[PDB]
Image 1 (cartoon, each protein chain N blue to C red):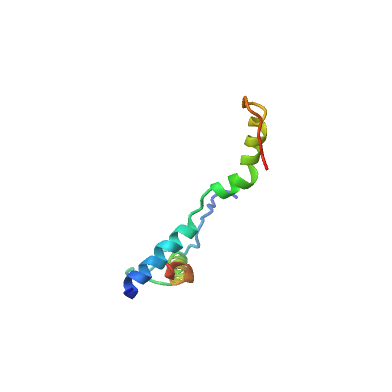
Image 2 (cartoon, helix red, strand yellow):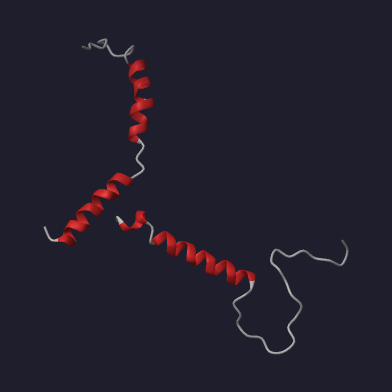
Length: 50
Length: 49
């Protein structure tokens, strides 16, 4: 629809006061879970044997 | 045998068991065909028991 754009990630309006790093954004969540999974992989039995 | 080495030995043996080689498949499925064809080519036919 005219004057609209789509965006692969969730989005928010521009913040009001100063910015700062946060940890509840979609990307941050994606990062944390991904790392958590691979850590689980590394500790799996398949790695331990070798 | 010191366990560190003992740990190493079982490790390297495990690695060998995990290699995704193609040979076992070839033996079971493809090698027989090659023999069956070549049997008609050699100057001496196969002689088996």
